[PDB]
Amino acid sequence: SLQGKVALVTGASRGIGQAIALELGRLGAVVIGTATSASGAEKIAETLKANGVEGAGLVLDVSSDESVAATLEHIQQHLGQPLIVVNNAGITRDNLLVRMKDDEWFDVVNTNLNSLYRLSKAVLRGMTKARWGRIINIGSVVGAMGNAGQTNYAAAKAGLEGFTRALAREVGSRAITVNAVAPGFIDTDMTRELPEAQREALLGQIPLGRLGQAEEIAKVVGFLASDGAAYVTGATVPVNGGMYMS
Amino acid sequence: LYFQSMSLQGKVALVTGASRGIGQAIALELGRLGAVVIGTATSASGAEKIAETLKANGVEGAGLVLDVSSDESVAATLEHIQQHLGQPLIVVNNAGITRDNLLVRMKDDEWFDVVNTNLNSLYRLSKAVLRGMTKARWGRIINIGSVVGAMGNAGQTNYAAAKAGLEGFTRALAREVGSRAITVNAVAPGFIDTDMTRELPEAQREALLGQIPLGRLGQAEEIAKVVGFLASDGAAYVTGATVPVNGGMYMS
Amino acid sequence: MSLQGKVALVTGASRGIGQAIALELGRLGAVVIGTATSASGAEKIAETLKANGVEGAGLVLDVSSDESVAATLEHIQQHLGQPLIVVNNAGITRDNLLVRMKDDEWFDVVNTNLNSLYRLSKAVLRGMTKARWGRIINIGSVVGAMGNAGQTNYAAAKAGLEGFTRALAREVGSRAITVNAVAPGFIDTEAQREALLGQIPLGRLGQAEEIAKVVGFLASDGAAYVTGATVPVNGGMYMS
Amino acid sequence: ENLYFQSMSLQGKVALVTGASRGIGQAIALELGRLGAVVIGTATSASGAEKIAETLKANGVEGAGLVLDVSSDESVAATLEHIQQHLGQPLIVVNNAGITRDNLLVRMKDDEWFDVVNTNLNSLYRLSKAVLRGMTKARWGRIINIGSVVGAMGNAGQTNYAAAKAGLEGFTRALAREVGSRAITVNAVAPGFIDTDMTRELPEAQREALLGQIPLGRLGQAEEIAKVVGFLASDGAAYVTGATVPVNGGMYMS
Ligand SMILES: NC(=O)C1=CN([C@@H]2O[C@H](COP(=O)(O)OP(=O)(O)OC[C@H]3O[C@@H](n4cnc5c(N)ncnc54)[C@H](OP(=O)(O)O)[C@@H]3O)[C@@H](O)[C@H]2O)C=CC1
Ligand SMILES: NC(=O)C1=CN([C@@H]2O[C@H](COP(=O)(O)OP(=O)(O)OC[C@H]3O[C@@H](n4cnc5c(N)ncnc54)[C@H](OP(=O)(O)O)[C@@H]3O)[C@@H](O)[C@H]2O)C=CC1
Ligand SMILES: NC(=O)C1=CN([C@@H]2O[C@H](COP(=O)(O)OP(=O)(O)OC[C@H]3O[C@@H](n4cnc5c(N)ncnc54)[C@H](OP(=O)(O)O)[C@@H]3O)[C@@H](O)[C@H]2O)C=CC1
C-alpha cells in the first residue's frame, strides 16, 4: 500500500515510533527512522533489516534548528524525497506549574511543538512538487483533556493539533493531508516511568480496562498514510481506549 | 486457488442501506476484507440488487429488506439474520435520510421522520445485536454520522440534531460495552459524491467546493476504507471516537 | 436590570435548575413565565416568583405533546405577550443499560428532551424574527459530550440538543437571535459521592444558582456575539 | 465625595490585564474597572502605559498603566515584582497580549514562528507562574486566557498562531486541573473576528469575505469580548473551569 514511497519517522528507536517505522515498512515504504545518537541510528537500521524492511537510521535532534535543516537538506539532495513524515519524537518534563523550572517548560515546548515547524518546513517543497504527501503528528489525550503536573506537555500537544488543522488548510490543494493521532496511555518507556499505584489508577479511567500497545498506534498511523485515507485531513484521531471521548 | 485470509475473515457484518452510495461501498469493502456481508435496502428489489452486487464482486453474504425506522422490520430482519447466517459481530449503522427545511417552514413529519430514521434506528439496531457481541467478547459498532452534527447547517436542524445525537449515543454505549472488547465509533463524512449530495442544487454544490481545502467531494470508497479500518483489530484501542472524513471542510 | 421589558419563558421551572433560572431572569428584570407538567407545579411557580418579587406566571405545559405546546404558546402570544427569551430546560431520564432498556425508556427521553426543542422553537421564532432580537438557550448536560453508561438515551438526546443549537444559530443569526446551550455537570439537586467528587477539579457539586448565572449572562445584551456555543458548567469534570 | 454607589461583582479585586493599551485588552480593563476591580493594564511602551493610566482615570477607575513585554523572562519578572511591591496581588489575571506574524509555512521565517509561540504561548507560563502563589493564599483566583477561533478552526497562513492559540487552550485545561482545589478557575475566551487593529489590518476584500462566513453578519466589538471576560471573572462563573468560550458570531461552532 506504500510501495515506492519514502517515509521519515522521528523517534524510531523504541516505543510508538519504532512500531510506526516497522508498520510503514510492512506496508512497503522505504523507512528513514531517527534517533538522538549515532548508536541509536545504527540500531534502527539493523532493526529494520532484521524485520525485512528497507531503509536507514538517521541521527536527528528535532529540538535543534541546525540538526533538522542540515540533515534534511542532505537526505533530499542525495538520498530522496520523504513523502510520508511522522512527527513522533516527544518528551515529558512533569511538574506542578509552581514547581516547574524554566528549562522544563521550554524544553517540552521546543521539542514537542517547535519541532513540527522545523520538520514540516524542510519536507513541504518536495510534497508540493509531487502533488502528494502525508504528515502525521503524534499528539496525546493530555492535549484535549489536560492533566495536572503537565501544563507544558498539554500546551505543546494541544498546539500540535492547532498546527495540524492550519497546515491541512494550506496544503490541501496539493493533495497533501495533515493529521494527528492522539494516543491515550500506551505501554512504552514513557509510561513505565509513572509510579505503580498511578498506573493502577489510570486503568480505572479506561473503558477497555487495559493500556494500549504501541502496535495499535502504528496501525492507525499506517492507515492514515495510505491512499484510502486521502479524504481525511485536519483530523485528530484519538486512540485512548475510551479514556477521553470528544 | 486459496487466497490469504484478510483482516475480517469469517466475521458476520451487517451494513444498513447497502443498496447504493456510502453503504454499498462499505459492504464491498468489508467483503474485500473477508467478512460475510449482509447488506440491506428498504425494498425487495433493492435487496435482490444487493445480492447480485455481492455475488458479482465475489463476496459471501445476503441482501435483505430492512426499514430501520420500524420496530417490526428490525425485529423480523435481525431474527432472519440470526437464523440463516449467524450473529453479526460488525454492525454499520449507515441508513439515513434528509428532509431539509428552515425550522419555521418545517413540517412535523420532516422533523420526526429524520429523528426516527437517523437516531432512533441506533437504539433499534444496537439493542438487537449487543447480546451476541457481549457473549463473543468482541464486536464493532460503527455509526455513520455527518459533519453537520458538529458544524450545524441552516435548513438542517432535524438532521443536525439526529447526527449530533448519534455521536452522544456512540460515546455512551462505548462506556457500557468496553469491558467486553466491543468498540463503538462514529465516522462523520463531509460531502461525498452520492445520490444524497447529487440532490442539492448545482449552485450549492459549486459553493461547496470553495469550502473544502482538498477542492473536491469525497468518494464513497473513501468513507468505506475508514470504516473497514475501524472494523479491524488494528483499531481495537479506538472507542467512543468520531473520525471526520470531510476533506478539511471542518476541523474539530 | 439587564432584561427589563422582556418576557422570558422557562420550561421545567418548578424546582432545581429551572427554578433557579426563572428566579435569575426575574432578578434581571424579565417578566417570567415558568412551566410545569402539573397544576401543583404551575401554582408553585406563580407563588415562588411572587415570594421573590418577580413578575410572571406559572403555566401547565407538556413539552412532549405537539398539541399542548402549539396551542398553549399560541394562547400566550395572543393574550399575555411575546417571549423573546426562551429557555428549554424541561428534561427527563430513564436510565438502563441498553441491553435492558425498554422501548418507552428510549422513546420518552428522545421525545421529551430532544423533540421538545423543535416544538418550542417553532412556536416562538416568528415573534423573535419580527422583534429582530431573541435568545434561545437550551439546557443540555455534560453527559451529552462525555457519555455515561446506563444513559445512552439521555446522552443521545442531550448531544442532539447541541447539534440542534448549532444548526438553528446558523438559521436565525441574520435576525440578531442567538441560540446557545449550557451543559451542567453534577449539581446539588456517601461512598460513590466521594468517587464522583474525585472526578471534579473544584472538588464540589455545583449549585443550581451557578447554572442560572450563566444562563442569565447568555440572555443579556453582553452576550450578543456568542451564538451556536455550548458553555460547560461542570467544575472541570469535562473540558472541551 | 458624598455619593456612594453599590459595590459591583469584582469590588476591590486587584486585576492584571496584559495589552490594555488598545483593542480587546483596553475594553477588558474598562469592563473589570466598571465592575469595581483595581485595574493594572500593561503596554509595550511608556507611551501606551501613560495612555492606560489616563483612560483609567478618565473612566474613574483606580489602577495603573505599566510597561510589560510578555515575551521577555526579565520584563515579566521585574514588572510582577513591582506590582507585588507597590500595587497589590493580582487575583484576576487576563492574558490578553498577543501578536500575529502571518505567512505560508514554506515562506515562514524562523523568527516569525518563534516570536508568535514565544509571545502568545510561552507568556502563559511566565505570567501564571508569577501570580499563582497569591491566588493560592487567598483561596480564590481567576486566570482568563484570550485564545482565538483560529486555534480550533485552523487558518492558512497562520500555522504559528494556530499552534500558539490551540496550545493556550491545552494549557488552560491542564492548569485548571492543578489549581481547582484552591477555588482558582482557569478559562479561555476565543474571539472570532473582532473590530480592532489586528483585524483592521486585513485587506478589505478578505474582511468582506469573512462576513459571508459569519451567521450574525458582522464583526464583533471589543466590548463584547470584555463582557464575557467580566462575567467569567465573577463568582457567577465559579463553577466554570477549563472551559473555552467561543465568541465568534457563529463563525465556528464546536
Ligand atoms: N507512551 C504513551 O502513553 C504516550 C505517548 N505519546 C507521544 O508518543 C510519542 C512517542 O512516545 P513513546 O514511544 O512513549 O516515547 P519514548 O520516550 O519511549 O521514546 C521517545 C522517542 O523520541 C525520541 N526523541 C526524544 N527527544 C528527541 C529529540 N529531541 N529529537 C529527536 N528525537 C527525540 C527518542 O530518541 P532516543 O531513543 O534517541 O532517545 C525516542 O525514539 C511522543 O510524542 C509522546 O509524547 C502520547 C500519548 C501517550
Ligand atoms: N452523501 C453525503 O455527502 C453524506 C452522507 N452522510 C450519511 O451517510 C449515510 C449514507 O449516505 P448516502 O450514501 O449519501 O445516502 P443515499 O441516500 O445515497 O443512500 C441511503 C441508503 O440508506 C437506505 N435507507 C434510507 N432510509 C432507510 C430506512 N428507513 N431504513 C433502512 N434503510 C434506509 C437507502 O435504501 P434504499 O436504496 O432502499 O432507498 C440507501 O441504501 C447516511 O446516514 C447519510 O446521512 C453523512 C454526511 C455526508
Ligand atoms: N482582533 C481579533 O479579531 C482577535 C483577537 N484575538 C486575540 O485577542 C488578543 C487581543 O487582540 P487585539 O486587541 O485585536 O490586538 P491589538 O493588536 O489591537 O492589541 C494587542 C495588545 O497586546 C499588546 N502586546 C503585543 N505584544 C506584546 C508583548 N510582547 N508583550 C506585552 N504586550 C503585548 C499590545 O501592546 P501595545 O499597544 O504596546 O503594542 C496591545 O495592547 C490577542 O491575544 C489576539 O490574538 C483573538 C481572536 C480574534
Image (cartoon, coloured by chain):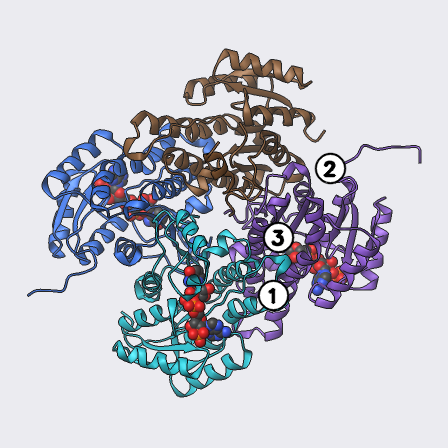
Chain colours: A cyan, B blue, C brown, D purple
Q: Which mark is residue D193?
A: 3
* Among numbered discs 1 and 3, the one appearing first in the sequence: 1
Note whether ligand 3 is within 8 Å of mark 3.
yes
Which residue is at the front of the view, C93 or A204? A204
Amino acid bearing label 3: Phe
Q: Which mark is residue D117?
A: 1
Q: D99 left or right of C129?
A: right
The subunit carrying tag 1 is D
Amino acid bearing label 2: Ser
* Among numbered discs 1 and 2, the one appearing first in the sequence: 2
Q: A217 left or right of D1?
A: left
> Where residue C174 appears, x then y in whole percent?
57, 40
Looking at the image, which residue sits at the far bottom?
A78
Looking at the image, which residue sits at the far left?
B1
**Is circle 1 on the same chain as circle 3?**
yes
Helix, strand, or loop for circle 1? Answer: helix
**Is circle 1 on the same chain as circle 2?**
yes
Crowding around mark 2 (Cα neighbors within 10 Å: few <14, some 14 to 19, many 20+) is: some
Amino acid bearing label 1: Val
Q: Which residue in the protein does label 2 denote?
A: D9
Residue that appears at 57% across and 56% down: D171
The subunit carrying tag 3 is D
